[PDB]
Amino acid sequence: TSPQLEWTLQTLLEQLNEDELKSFKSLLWAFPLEDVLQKTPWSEVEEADGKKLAEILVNTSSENWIRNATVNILEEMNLTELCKMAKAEMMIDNFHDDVTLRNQRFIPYTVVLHGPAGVGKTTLAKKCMLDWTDCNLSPTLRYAFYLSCKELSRMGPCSFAELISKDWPELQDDIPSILAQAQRILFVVDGLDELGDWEKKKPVPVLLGSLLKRKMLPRAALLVTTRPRALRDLQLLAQQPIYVRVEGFLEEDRRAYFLRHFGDEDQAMRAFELMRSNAALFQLGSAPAVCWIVCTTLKLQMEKGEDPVPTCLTRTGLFLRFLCSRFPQGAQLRGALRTLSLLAAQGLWAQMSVFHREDLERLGVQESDLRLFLDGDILRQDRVSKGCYSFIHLSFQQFLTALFYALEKEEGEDRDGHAWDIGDVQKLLSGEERLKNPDLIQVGHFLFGLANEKRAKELEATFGCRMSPDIKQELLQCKAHLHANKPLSVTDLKEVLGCLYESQEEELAKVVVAPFKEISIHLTNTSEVMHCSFSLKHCQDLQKLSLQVAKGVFLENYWARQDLRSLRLWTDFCSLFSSNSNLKFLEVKQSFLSDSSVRILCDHVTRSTCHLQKVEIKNVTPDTAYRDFCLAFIGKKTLTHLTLAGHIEWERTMMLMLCDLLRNHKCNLQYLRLGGHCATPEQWAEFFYVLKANQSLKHLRLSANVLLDEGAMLLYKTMTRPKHFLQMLSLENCRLTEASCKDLAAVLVVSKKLTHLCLAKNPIGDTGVKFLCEGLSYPDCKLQTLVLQQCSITKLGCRYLSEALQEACSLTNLDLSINQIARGLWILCQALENPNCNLKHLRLWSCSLMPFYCQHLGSALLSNQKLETLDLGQNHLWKSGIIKLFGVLRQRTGSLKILRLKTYETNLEIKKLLEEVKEKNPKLTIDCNASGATAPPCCDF
Amino acid sequence: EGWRNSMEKQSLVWKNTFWQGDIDNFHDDVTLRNQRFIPFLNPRTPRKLTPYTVVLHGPAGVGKTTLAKKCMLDWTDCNLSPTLRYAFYLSCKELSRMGPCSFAELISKDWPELQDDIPSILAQAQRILFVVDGLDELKVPPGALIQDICGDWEKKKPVPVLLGSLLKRKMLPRAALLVTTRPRALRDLQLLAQQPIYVRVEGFLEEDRRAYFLRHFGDEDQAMRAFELMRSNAALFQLGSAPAVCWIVCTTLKLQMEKGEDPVPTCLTRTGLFLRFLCSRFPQGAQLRGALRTLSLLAAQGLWAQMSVFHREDLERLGVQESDLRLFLDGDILRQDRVSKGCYSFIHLSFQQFLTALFYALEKEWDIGDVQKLLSGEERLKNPDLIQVGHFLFGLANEKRAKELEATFGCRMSPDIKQELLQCKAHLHANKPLSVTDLKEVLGCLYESQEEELAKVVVAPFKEISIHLTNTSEVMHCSFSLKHCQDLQKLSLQVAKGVFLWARQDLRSLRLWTDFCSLFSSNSNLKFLEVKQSFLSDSSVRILCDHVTRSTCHLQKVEIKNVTPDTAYRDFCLAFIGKKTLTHLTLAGHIEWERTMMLMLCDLLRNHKCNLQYLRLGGHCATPEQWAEFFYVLKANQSLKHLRLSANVLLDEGAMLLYKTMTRPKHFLQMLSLENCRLKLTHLCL
Amino acid sequence: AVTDHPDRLWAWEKFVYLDEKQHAWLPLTIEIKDRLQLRVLLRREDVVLGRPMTPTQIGPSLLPIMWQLYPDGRYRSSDSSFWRLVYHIKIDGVEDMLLELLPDD
Amino acid sequence: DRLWAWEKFVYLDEKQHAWLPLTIEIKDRLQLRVLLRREDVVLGRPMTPTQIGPSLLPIMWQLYPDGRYRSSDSSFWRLVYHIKIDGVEDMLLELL
Amino acid sequence: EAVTDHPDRLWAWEKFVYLDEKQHAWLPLTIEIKDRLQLRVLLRREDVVLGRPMTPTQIGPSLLPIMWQLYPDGRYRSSDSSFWRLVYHIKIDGVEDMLLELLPDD
Amino acid sequence: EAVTDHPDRLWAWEKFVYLDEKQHAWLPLTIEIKDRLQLRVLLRREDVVLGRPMTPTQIGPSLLPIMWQLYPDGRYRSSDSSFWRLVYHIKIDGVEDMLLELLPD
């Protein structure tokens, strides 16, 4: 498998907002799908977020299909900026041993190790080699050789036998004998990213490429260590390799390291708690060096009797304190600090992790300063290959890079004798540079963190340097990254909020969060809640909001202090609803809440400074949330919509609340939906009795609720009364049959207010259709809309419908789909020919029609005078049907305005016919892309 | 212009781009569907200087040559562009025979008129399109494609050298290349090609098969009936991705239905379907025995040497007469390729395999191996195409089919086929998890045979089995075959999602499940059962429990793991009360304790007929009161000896009650464990 | 004559059963002729609901704790015996049900 | 005077004449009705209490003043009526 | 004697019969009216048998709400959207008692 | 002291205010309940300014009726057709008070 493609596909998709992602899924579905994808259930695709969707595509579809599917879709959606990005890329002991022991077991064979820096891959390889030496491994390993790109990048051309025997001269006499047993040799290549005859002299790159290609000693064993950045080349070089991933320390090992370093249980546990309180700093604690830095700093502060709480609040404070605590007092080494910053910047830009004495000389780094640089633990000298140096850890290098950019620039520095490999602020903050070099993202956060004033003051006082004051403006000059004029995706919002929190200056947040108009949030831990609370309180024009809480934020229902901190932060966070008086739409979905949090949220929602106008709840746990929400939303003057869905059982308390919500006299509701509610016929009877008093409700949906047809008959017998007030009504998927249709016909004939209806997903049957049609025939019928999508109707039902329509009815809208009318299609065509028809719209999406029947539709369309829209999809009339329909309709200019069907625009004759029809009927719009596999829903009807 | 006019006449043969007899040319959509993935057919493609190579790969019979023809035709039209447009097409079928010559002479063999201008056309390399078709049908010595690579197109070299030059892009590097192959030969191109792009051809999908059925039959009722018949047999359904197989099935079923015979038996097994097809392609009383012998021998020859296309000389070597060729062609057995004269081939791969098997069965009176070689694992791994001949050979073992064939063609079947099949019986024993796939293969073979004696003899010695259902056909196979086992002692069952979800389909599924569950009641020696990671339904679970509760089952050790829906645990716990032989019982899963389940557990441990000697639980959540009642009832039990409550939420009061119970003298337990509870007697752990 | 038989029956209170739809059933009388002749007549009546008495509180009794229906029209109780349905008819809205005990082999 | 259970649903009196319970009626939680008949039936071995298993009726009955009966479980019963039909005696009791 | 625990709900099982979240019964004794906007209701604890649960139609119109509920800050929200304040909650002679008031609409 | 006179009829003018044929303002001060069938209410006569007549729709549902009637033999008729009884009507220190009662059907 190739981890590269999955990573590239994931990062692109996460830049899409909610609106664009929905279109992307629909457009992909219309794309020619490979046979494997179709087996997937469409429900899962809808619920999958950005990250999962990439996982689904990579695990089932061919590589080439993914590349062309992504590029084509983005180009059509007109996201030009993303298209360019896509095309460019698509073109101490007892612990390390504990980790390595389990790591080693996951492993001619080609093995590749990859992981983040500082996780200890070199220790793993050296442990394997030592085990070979100590006979710990199998005896089959008789010889092993060590090759390091850290050193081999400089040595000149020579023979492979000499190359490998350079460090062991005594073995050259035995090199031929050793290589006569290629099956007993192990080769290790360490640090690739830092970069046939064994007795033939050749260049080192050629030798390395040949060995990696197995052109020399093919039957040996290879083991490669590299960072994910350089993993691309091994794909073009290696043949059928296997990839292994390393992880490093865990929480338990971090605790153990802290216990070892501190010694005292109290100090160690206090420090560990203070560190873990910060999720972002905790994650970077996997690398041992970061834990070393944290322990040293906190211990030094504790021994001096200082408060450590501010230190761990954000990364930049911690690193800044450590750096301030590693140089002598009174020196004011301005020059040394500038030199170190420049060196780190150069190193980061060039993607190099090691430097030789020559490199330090090239930059004018006096070797005397190396004493301070080393004894302070900023640089670490390698003790294996002399003449090498490296930085303590990657994050420290990034921090020094940021310090370079915020440092004041001197006049004429462009006149230096070297062309430095340093960019500028705008280039640093550009997205293409981020994708090309993923190691600048962290420099971004650190730079934001250094925009504070107090930190600059302290740094200048301790060292005596001078700080550039234009950073506050340079950061905002890249404000176009934020002023996209569209709601930002979840990941972008997380990044922006994190940076703003790092800044710790509200004046920087105000100018940035002022123009937000819509927001989506996905909380996963406490730190995210704290960031959102700190930043979003300044919004004033916010108008929509979608919330979601992941498991683990709130502790399971029964630790008390751990939940108390979360409760406090939640209470602080829930002040958006009460303060902002422009918010006008909310939504909550798939949240693992707890009773106390729900109660706090409702307390804040019940105040009189909130002006909500729509609400939605979906799949929330526990199950008291629905009852509490129904209680809280009683009497809301502004509320005019409300939705509830999930799996519930009608406890008597819920029935009380859900009847009182309609009994009230302040009620202003105008639309109410219910889902997954199971109850006995008595409760339903009393509910429908309560409905009789309401004088504001207009819609009513009951999707996924069980009526058992007894609630349905009770409902109909309630509606036959002369003073009901409902107008719309929908009984989608309520376990209906033909038994109740007679009462429905009675309602239709007697009613005087009903003017819409819907019965999707119900096999009522042709007998039910017959009963309804008997109902429609009465002169005084007022129903104007009717929906019978996917109701298992046959040609007898079609005949009944045509017989009903043949009279002067009032129906104008009719929607049929899934259920098929092909054989009886001529019957409905005859009905359309009748002058008494008054239909304006008609939908026949996926009705299994054959091209032979196009004649009837053509004649009817040429004859009718009132039809104004027809919808055909998923039919087999694509070629012959197109030809015949276009030929027939070329004769007359009918009233039809919108016609939808699926076509291929690659045919010349079809194009000519379409052009002729359009020229003779310029007022007719024809949709040629009906391939969409999403049916017209019932939301409008 | 003048060149195009001459080419337009040749465009007529390539314009037969739809299946012979297709109704309204259904292949148009299928061909045009995949045209979106070819680089040099996209004007949007960046105009770089790198030349590309496109490699088409897909199983046999999916029709890739048709897509290549469509690409050539599209290229010929050539919407006005400054560059010129020329197209040429080389087939590997005739390359393996041609002698040494230059590339210009090689490409001018079929274009004598343009020969004098061919050098000029070659000079304008940019305006050239090359199609190399049939890389799996190339016969060359080993490594001959990497010898003395030549760069000049007018220098005379051996044909393999010319190929190694062109594919490796050492000569005419600026032209466009299209290589077609089957998956067998996907290894050479990894070496020869530089920067390749792979395109996959898959042929008809389900909806396309439905459309083909509707267009062929004409009447909706018959078409849907036949489609359901086909979809019944999943294995025969998969071969429905090739148009030729669908054509065969439709012709056979339509002809049968027209005369009024029962069509259900025909689609019950592949071999029956093909035998019915074959029996109706010659006039009755024709005495074609010699013809059938020759055809069987020819099919065997072809499949053994891995050759799929025969020339007239190859048919001559076997003495096939022009009459025999006419009878085969008119009967839709051989198809004469239209483009390159002198090439024939069988209607599909599967028909060739079946005819080969007929050679093995037929009685005796060339490079063809023996039965032991045919069934040898090494030969199978070397040449995977010989697998299907095994199933066809098994199917032909039936006596009724042999009698039908004998009465039809007057041939004679060798009576030793049964014994020869049985001799290889030893190869099948695996008695391990590897037996899963081997068990599937053996069950498929036996179900093909349709004779109970063979199954009886074959499956006698089994002791341990594993089953992994994924569709209805597997359940049918298992029910038909396993019933004869008598020494079975262990059984592990697993059902995959999708077997259970339309009323007719649900009825069929329930009936087949009811037939399958009869194993437990009829077989007595069975003593160990296990179910894990299954997706069941209420009715199936109830049927299983009803069969387990009977008085013949003698189970002793039962395990349940990760079953859905959650009611299954309740039902299984209810059904296991009083089964004296039961001694061990385990339950694992995630579910909340309902009052009813609490009552069931209490009763299960309270009954005086209980004889359990061990019990383990896991993943259960309840309040302290329910645990208190559970432990209070447990005091009344005097048979249970071992207990383990690992990985359960529990409560502090429940843990305290358990601790008190352990030290209480009355309690008869000997070992206990309350692992992972939010933290007589010989062993104890908390 | 009722065709839809109940799917489950649980003992909620001494001499009170709740069905799958939570309608209280009451056993009227137990008729016994000998050890092998036992039958009980059940009737449907809406009665006030108390608290669910635990099994320890119900105490020993002849009848089983709960019932369950298996295909082929037979009833299996938690005590491992099979009950055969005799008749189930509806008269003026009141439903009568009689069950018989099959002596297990 | 007293009734001793010899077999399931079989009771022997002070004179060792068998009494066979016939029916058990429940009207309300506190209303339990049982009818007793005296008829000589072939007796088997004494079913020890464990063999009898759970049962609603008590194991022993003893006469109590006020037309009442005391059971082995300390519960009390009331005698409703007692007649003789065709030589067969009948006894009906109701729970208290 | 002051009490530091409060009920988190009060359903209306029957008119003048409320059951808290632990299925204990509260009974209202008297209703006080001082003026139009001041109403103070007195609840008492007592154990009594429960009949069938009267349904909302049978309950009919009333001055008291159908269900209270505790909200942070120590205020109850009735079912008519009005807030009720807690006055006092003491124990005397082993008898629980509570007093609640109707705050002016905000 | 007890007073023989009493309003013949009472009508509700505002929220928790009534008027008699004399148009005296009678108001409710306390309500005492012992059970559903036992309900008591207290009335007092005070002088206050009357606003616009709050029509019954605005008054909203209440435990007290919209109209109270008086009949001999201690019989009072309400708007909802229920019956009430008078216990005492006295005047002390210048304040006039009246007590009502509810009688079970």
Image (cartoon, coloured by chain):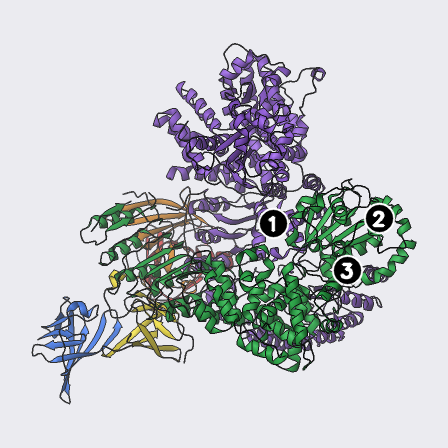
Chain colours: A purple, B green, C yellow, D blue, E orange, F red
Which circle marks residue A926 in the picture?
Answer: 3
The residue where tag 1 is placed is A57
CA neighbours of label 3 inside 10 A, class few (<14), some (14 to 19), many (20+)? some
Give yes or no for contact between labels 2 and 3 (Cβ–Cβ under 8 Å): no
Number of numbered discs overlaid on the protein picture: 3
For label 1, the SS is helix
Using the image, name the chain to which the residue with label 3 belongs.
A
Task: Work out which residue is located at the far front of the displayed protein and give it.
Answer: B365
State whether discs 2 and 3 lie on one chain: no
Res A120 seen here:
no
Residue type pointed to by label 3: Ile
Across and down, in percent, residue B590 comes to 41, 53
- Give the CA distance from mark 2 to mark 1: 46 Å
Task: Work out which residue is located at the far right of the displayed protein and give it.
Answer: B2
**Residue A94 higher or lower than B386, as above or below:** above
Res B110 seen here:
yes
Residue type pointed to by label 1: Leu
| Viewer-side residue, B245 vs A496 | B245
Between disc 2 and disc 3, the foreground one is 2
Across and down, in percent, residue B270 comes to 58, 69
CA neighbours of label 2 inside 10 A, class few (<14), some (14 to 19), many (20+)? some
**Residue D39 higher or lower than A880, as above or below:** below
- Give the CA distance from mark 2 to mark 3: 52 Å
- Does label 1 or label 3 sit earlier along the sequence? 1
Which circle marks residue B104 in the picture?
Answer: 2
Using the image, name the chain to which the residue with label 1 belongs.
A
